[PDB]
Amino acid sequence: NDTVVVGSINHTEQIIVANMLAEMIEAHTDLKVVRKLNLGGVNVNFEAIKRGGANNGIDIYLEYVGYGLVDILGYPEPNVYIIADKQKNGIKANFKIRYNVEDGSVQLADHYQQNTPIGDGPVLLPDNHYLSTQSVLSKDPNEKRDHMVLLEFVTAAGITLGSMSKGEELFTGVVPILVELDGGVNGHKFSVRGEGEGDATNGKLTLKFICTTGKLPVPWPTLVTTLVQCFSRYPDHMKQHDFFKSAMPEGYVQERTISFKDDGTYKTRAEVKFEGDTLVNRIELKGIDFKEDGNILGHKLEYNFPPPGATDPEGAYETVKKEYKRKWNIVWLKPLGFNASYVLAVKDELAKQYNLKTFSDLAKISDKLILGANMMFLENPDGYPGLQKLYNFKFKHTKSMDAGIPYTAIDNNEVQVIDATATDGLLVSHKLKILEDDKAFFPPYYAAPIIRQDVLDKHPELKDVLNKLANQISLEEMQKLNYKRDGEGQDPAKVAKEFLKEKGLI
Image 1 (cartoon, rainbow, N blue to C red):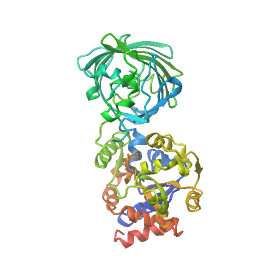
Image 2: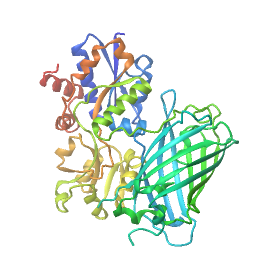
Image 3: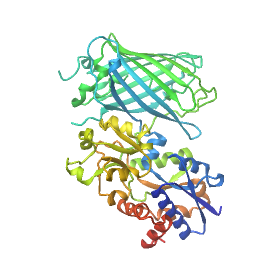
């Protein structure tokens, strides 16, 4: 090799830092650096780097730990938001599940869920909250049948600090569980049976499943969500939000639509109820329009669910590095220093007129306020609808604005709240208050360069050269650099080069 390709998307911080990476490589090596702009969606850099520099892709770019974890890998298993569904006298949920593919890619399955009580009496209808599941899938080494051993921990959270429904009394001990599933996928009939126990006090479930008709025609991981949320641990101050146990012993119907991106659809209908002492989940599943050689019917998914992968930024970085390496032979280098997390911004004055310290405070005053957000933040499911689920934001008029017209808007007080990233320098110049994500809906976005192992094999010096930037850019420094371009109009290449010169890095 003789050239390496550094990519950016058409955004200020990306162009500045990409220029910095290029300047560092040129100052400390004898390589020629191609500077390649990518247009479009937020994962165009990732697609480019999988292409590689030799195929009109890129070799290097700045990625963010939290985006790699949450949006690409789908780690850890998602929080599943439980929302009351009046029309069903029950609850509903919408969430995304990701499965690892054997070629390294990631398969998405959009889940849509509705639950309805079987009995005629009153049930608990919850305020917005979420269930957090950790799933461990394993094999019984001795077992000849097609099977899945499953352990799960499930906890309700998201609401901060009689006393339980009558149905909850059925869950104080260890409850035997029976699961029965009859299915057809593209007309391939199959049946699954599972046995085990649930211990809601510890939010713990243990089950073994066997396919009773021979080979399972779909991968076991795609059946986990289908194969008993009544075993969640609700903390004491939240037990009034446990619909699932309040419907017991008569039970509830659970219906899902599961849409696999670029593949078929599952529809499921299940009854979850006590039969004698046993909690039974009986399911009918029908899968339609699957590719016989796609990821599901072709059995191209890995046998696993997301790792626990300790949640502090050190653990997040370790997991994202391990997995990018394993899945795509992409190498995360050291973090630059700044955390470019999503925040909401209000006027500095309107803020301490209501003592706005966190996102909760803004939600309490949210009726009086309008939110002029950006459009690929309003539309993204992972974006503002999820944040609304966790905070119950009553911005009953919010505007879908494109580029930084929202800044003039909040200055014009057309609008009271805007969405921003913590490194936007225009937040300082515009006199704005960054509110804290106190319930931590957004993961940290620590920025780091990433590079193909491809390119490091041919030019090992790149690893140390790019790591010369480790911890060299604080959040305040990134804000100032971004301001030089956005607020002062300076050339981003000159901004990058001058910053490196002044620090003695080139």
